[PDB]
Amino acid sequence: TFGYVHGVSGPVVTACDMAGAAMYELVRVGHSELVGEIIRLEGDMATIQVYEETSGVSVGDPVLRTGKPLSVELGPGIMGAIFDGIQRPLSDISSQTQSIYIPRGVNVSALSRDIKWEFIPSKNLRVGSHITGGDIYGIVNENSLIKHKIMLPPRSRGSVTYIAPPGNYDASDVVLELEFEGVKEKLSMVQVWPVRQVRPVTEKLPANHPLLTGQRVLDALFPCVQGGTTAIPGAFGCGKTVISQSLSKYSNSDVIIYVGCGERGNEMSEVLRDFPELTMEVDGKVESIMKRTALVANTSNMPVAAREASIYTGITLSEYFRDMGYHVSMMADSTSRWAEALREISGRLAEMPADSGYPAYLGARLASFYERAGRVKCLGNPEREGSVSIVGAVSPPGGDFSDPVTSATLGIVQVFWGLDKKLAQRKHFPSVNWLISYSKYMRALDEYYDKHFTEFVPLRTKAKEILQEEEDLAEIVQLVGKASLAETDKITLEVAKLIKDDFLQQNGYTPYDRFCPFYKTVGMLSNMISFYDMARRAVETTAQSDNKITWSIIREHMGEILYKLSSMKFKDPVKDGEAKIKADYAQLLEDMQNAFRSLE
Amino acid sequence: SLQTSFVTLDEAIKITNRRVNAIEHVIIPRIERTLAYIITELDEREREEFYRLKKIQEKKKIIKEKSE
Amino acid sequence: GLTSEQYHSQVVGKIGYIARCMQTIDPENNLKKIREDYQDVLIWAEKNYRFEEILEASKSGKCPNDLDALSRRSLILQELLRLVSSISPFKMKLDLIESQYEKMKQHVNLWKSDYHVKLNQLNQLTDYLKNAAPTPKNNFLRAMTSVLQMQIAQYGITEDNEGINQLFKLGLHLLAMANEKIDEQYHLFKGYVKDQPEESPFEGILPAEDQKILVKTMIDYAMP
Amino acid sequence: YLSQPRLTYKTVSGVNGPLVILDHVKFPRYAEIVHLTLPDGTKRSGQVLEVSGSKAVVQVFEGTSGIDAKKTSCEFTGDILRTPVSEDMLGRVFNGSGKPIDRGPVVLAEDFLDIMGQPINPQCRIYPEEMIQTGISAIDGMNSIARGQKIPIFSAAGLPHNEIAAQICRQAGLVKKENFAIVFAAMGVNMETARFFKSDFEENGSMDNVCLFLNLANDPTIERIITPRLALTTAEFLAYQCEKHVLVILTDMSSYAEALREVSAAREEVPGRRGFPGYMYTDLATIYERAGRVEGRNGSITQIPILTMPNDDITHPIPDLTGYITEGQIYVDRQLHNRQIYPPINVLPSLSRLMKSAIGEGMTRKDHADVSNQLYACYAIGKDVQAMKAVVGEEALTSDDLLYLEFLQKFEKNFITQGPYENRTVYETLDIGWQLLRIFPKEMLKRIPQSTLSEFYPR
Amino acid sequence: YLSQPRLTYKTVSGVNGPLVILDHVKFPRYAEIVHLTLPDGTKRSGQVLEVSGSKAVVQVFEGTSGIDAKKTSCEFTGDILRTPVSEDMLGRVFNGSGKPIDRGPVVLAEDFLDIMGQPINPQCRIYPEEMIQTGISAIDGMNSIARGQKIPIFSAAGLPHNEIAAQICRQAGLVKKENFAIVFAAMGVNMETARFFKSDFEENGSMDNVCLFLNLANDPTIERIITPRLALTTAEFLAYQCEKHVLVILTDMSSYAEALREVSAAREEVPGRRGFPGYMYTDLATIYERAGRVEGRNGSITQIPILTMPNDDITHPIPDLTGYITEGQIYVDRQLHNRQIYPPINVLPSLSRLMKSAIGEGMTRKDHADVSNQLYACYAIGKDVQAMKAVVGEEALTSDDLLYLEFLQKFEKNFITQGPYENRTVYETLDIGWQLLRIFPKEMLKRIPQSTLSEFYPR
Amino acid sequence: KDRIEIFPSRMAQTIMKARLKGAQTGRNLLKKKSDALTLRFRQILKK
């Protein structure tokens, strides 16, 4: 169980005298017990990937072999904490070591063992009863927002021989003891689960409820669904960070996880500065966002192995809370940094690469991450159903989707919110191409929309028709200067501008557009299309007659109607009431109908 | 209105045909030469990657033989 | 997506779960039809079989080993239990329990039913109140919740009674209302209580202490 | 049968990524199937990729995590991967490895076939004849599929190529102027789409004639390579031994190609053009060409491979190498999709080289060939006139140009736009064609002989 | 105190390029340091790149010429290159290995620091906010720089990136409503540039707070791999222990990247794009990220590295990987330089990530954010107008295009063009911004809220 | 001059191919404009 170092080359350490080792077992290399894992074995020599700096490691240093793969401690004390890429609490390292630096070989327990937790049993689990994996036998009140439910670890079952009474217990106390085939397993509030293992569920279910966000361009055109898998290409100022924050604060979800893979030092600080300071309204009260959020922090100057493992740590936490019946929304900062880590390690291991230096299995690693999501029926007696949504983020070397990471992502993710370079240059925010983007959940959400709204589906169809028709008319207008256009074509161009500027564009730092509720998004679109249909009907109905109606006549006749339509973004939800906003939009529709009636 | 609407058509045609001719004789040929240049140079970069990867595989084979 | 061992283990748990839910919802065995409709799994409980023996009985095909069918039947019982246990004080009649059981059982997919949503809304209101200060808003939510819990016990949750329908909308609308907006908090509560067919919608179901708090609360708001 | 007891080895020389290197193995075969038992009792499957003396190298299908070099045992079967085939497996759903995932039993075999098979002897290959209608007008009256050809659907990422594939499975069948089956294989499919395929086939009653293979994006990447081989092995059994016509749809061949690249890397082969193996051409031909009619038998196999074009560039090796060895293309566009037209199939860039033999009297209807050619010309002209309109305006157009614009608008609305649940047989598609063609007076239908016009044009 | 005698070896196995391979070494320590004494007495040093068994590969900084394989003596220090550092290193010039070149003594070891870097706990990292007023309108107006930022200057060969960097150094300061120490790492810099910077610091009287590390183009190319680590190690001492604010200038990360490539090739490592090591990303991240503020300290490190872009592109791996690590760039262009514009900075491909937070009411001016965005968009449009004009001619533009063209021409003449010996404040820069914005009628300024326009626009 | 002088890349291929398609579309649309003007010119000529 104590091997020796045979040869260090970068973060890759060759060991010897490890005949019984298995792949991806954790090892501690060196006299500082640096964290590493076995990547491959040749005879009794192991090739170890180290998660820390290897400077100073000598030939002959000891290697301590453990029997567990890279795993996360799952239990009370996660929410509000920031973890390293391999599950190391940064706030506890700072306070326990009293230094700005992270020591090499530091061993801080992932979940503090000195905190008294309030544990409440299920109050029906009698001694002698039968339990299986996933069963919930008590709750811990971490805070007023998220109740932490204590699950039996997966792959365990048996008869209950002891259950702790209501009281305050630490993370090292025995709460439940169960016996299976004569073996007595004593469990605390913390379970351990390998990061590369998928937590089992009873059934993976279709995603039929939307994950509403604050951006109209997204929800009106390319919806994301609870349990959906999407990606948002990286682009500064284009809304990448507005969606991350809005998604955390306003979205239809219970637990938020934000995982960095290769974040820049100061960008990581920005997230950490905002994390305890952002708040949300829960039930009439304002509460800190950190109470329902737990991020994983990993910067570009961290070891390549932790850069790779960060994603696995994040999704492991996500599935853990998924199995509580919560709706979990996991945001990645970058998956291109993950792919970069894979390229770096593939090179270091001297294995045959594929396109642009990436490993040929890049697609398999991304699929493994992206497919660990969806609405599920959870294991355990309570029959609860949770979900994980994944939002990926592919940093664009360009708009060419030949990019190995973009291409592999596109083949897996159901929703792709591509960010146009030209819209970014023009400071059109959020910057979404809306011609190259897609969402494959249309038919899944059609049931929802038809049940609740009935109006959105047909409005969505017409809106997409107008935007695409505008692009084709734009191509010729740039050439001939509108010298010859049909009257209907002139309306399409002008309504499409109304849509582009006053519906698909919003300033997410303003009270009025920090979050636009879906009922309002539908209201806005309903009026703009209603205008379109009435303007198109008027000119086509009166065409080839005496009192020919044109756009110039409509704009002069009811110019205040276009002003009101362009003003709809300013109704300011939450400060103003839902009942009034609906009434105000109803008035705009009545005024347009009367304006066209008097025109015709 | 014939003659005054006619020479203006002859001028409009001469301007339009000149632009069309430039697209055909100047701008597209230039784009096609650029594209063909790009295609060739990219295959040249592919080759030098092939060379290095082949030599890497041979060096690994040599190391493996020495180990036996 | 389970292994052969995980599948049968999960079945053993659910079998024991139904037995425990049955004793919890009907500790006196008053619901004869409900117990018989689960006899094929209850026969494997209420006796000392040992986990291992039921696991083998599942593997050999002696226990109802269809996990999806067992989940379907288990969920209907659990949701009926939530209906009964989500209203601790006010008791539901045995006929209403069997009647609503049949309706839950006949529903194609209970999890996405209106019954499920209404039960979730009820638990949202009751869970907030269990951990709340006696503020004007929270005294109003308590008062309205007691009525909602009473009406559900009397009429059932599967029935679209106008009483519980109004109460759900107003209770949740108040719950989400900002804590500082005292005038809106009272306006909603006053609106509800005055627009009822009863002279005293809270009589009997609320103890004298809660009714006195409500009277003092409305006086403290409006008197100054 | 072999009747030779299996040998199980605990001798492991090392483990390197997906590969386990064994030692002291007795007369190992290449492509041999073996089973691993890990110290935790976990079982895994694998296949022998290299046998250098006694040092057999096996690729493990599942992940290699947890495998040691001291206790893990490897049981050799003594044979290669042979798939149990039967007629009864039609109506079943399998995963990439050939295992049921529909809660039914394991296949009760009628025979065992090597999934790699053999090429069909060209001397007995019969040129394609009759038509297999798909139910989708855009590809029945314009680019029909002959009973024996291989015509791919090229689509960009994000387009509804899977919804069309499902629609073909529900609607496709014989012309019917009981012996038709569809074998559907999805490679690298994500969980949401896998559910779509499985449920959509079951709910609409089509499953009785569908054999469905699902290889999910998170399934073993080597299994993705045999997946289409299992689908084709089944198709060959059903088609050629049981005298019936089999339509084989291979969805997301681009994901297959990516898995093939991974296998090449596992062998430490030097990548070829754009990172893909130098043998990608022969590998795709090995799959595609196991189709067509054969002399002396009444069965047939057709294929509709469906391919995502990276960066929407037809030049990319995947659609390029496919198109080079297939007969025409369907071609799904983006503009039609953004305009909310379903199906979004563009008839102008599409081609079916075998249409000449697929259609005509005795196969569909007398007027089939003539209607197709005239509709193509009218659509091409309508697009040309529409482009002109954008320059000269509505008032500058003559009556003939306006008729072509009327055709263009009604062609896309009536002929191309269909919906996923409307099944248009070949005869209704042609009747719709005539309704659109009767927009024009007879003298403008230059590509339809006068005899055809006099019979079909009126009424 | 490591009071253990060091072993000295003559057991040289061989020498291959910049690498010396030793055998029979007792317990080799990774990244250890070896002192080499050549047969003629010349002393040189090197650092271990890898160890295996009794063998070690040593990277020799000064070069390997003259080393034999029989007599060269190799002394293993037993430790990692921890470099002597002192607060009085300011006012000194060192060579690329940290030795005196200025006729002063060897730096007295006030303490030792491991040049590899000690990672800073992100939890204690303090987000930068205060804006640095560089004097350059292209930076202070649009792409503002916060103290603690990492904003490298991209340029191609021949461009005046040395003048811009020198201008920033002598004009550096804070936005007022006391100054920086300079740590200057020269890697592969020619003598003409070396004296340019040295003289500029002297002429402005800055040397009292300047520490130079000079590895010139005619100096050894392996040494420069450590040079930047020595420079930043001193910066970290001065900023985080001596409570100074340090501005760090790295004259070329491209010659650094090339030096890594030379070593990577020498040890037969598997390259990535364009022959550079697959781990270039990490080797850069471990230098770039040595910046910012930490809780409990008052000092800071601001980095402004320079990178020469091969072939004038910005997709070369060197600037490509840097862009992913650093927080924006300046991007010095060539088209502006050819037109005799200085500083020739192109505002479109250049961004500053911290700009959105280091500006606004309480830090600069209420309108700062709005002016920047509007000017940027107008510039971007102006460039699209030129793209059209080049085809259609100046006689085929509309009134709005002419306003954007006039803006573009005046923007570069009045805003970007400055001169190397004139500084303008952020408030003066915005006032000029408005003069350019007031070219347009208010109706066209669609990226500025109406409230801002009414306050500023009519002035 | 002879080339647009964009450094070889897959991104350049995408940009150049889109630029070529744009130029070809403009060529065809302007050719139709010329043909329309030429017909009108000749008609005016006949009258």
Image (cartoon, coloured by chain):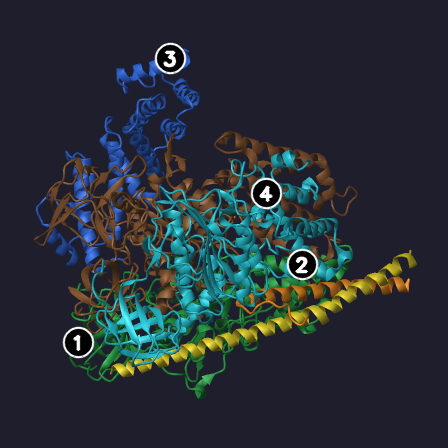
Chain colours: A brown, B yellow, C blue, D green, E cyan, F orange
**Disc 3 and disc 4 on one polypeptide chain:** no
Cα distance in 3D space between marks 4 and 2: 23 Å
**Disc 4 and disc 1 on one polypeptide chain:** no
* Mark 2 residue crowding within 10 angstroms, few (<14) / some (14–19) / many (20+): few
Can you tell which quarter of the image residue F5 is in?
bottom right
- Residue E304 visible, this angle: yes
Q: Is residue D417 left or right of residue C86?
A: right
Q: Amino acid at mark 2?
A: Gln
Cα distance in 3D space between marks 4 and 1: 78 Å
**Disc 2 and disc 3 on one polypeptide chain:** no
Cα distance in 3D space between marks 2 and 3: 80 Å
The C terminus of chain A sits in image quarter: top right
Identify the residue shown where x is 34% and y is 69%.
Answer: E46
Please give the residue where the numbered disc 4 appears in the rendered image.
Answer: E425
User: Which disc number belongs to residue C219?
Assistant: 3
- Residue E357 visible, this angle: no
Cα distance in 3D space between marks 3 and 4: 62 Å
- Between tags 2 and 3, which lies in front? 2
Q: Amino acid at mark 4?
A: Thr
Marks 2 and 3 in Cβ contact (< 8 Å): no
Most foreground residue, B67 or E420: E420
Q: Chain of mark 3?
A: C
Identify the residue shown where x is 26% and y is 44%.
Answer: C75
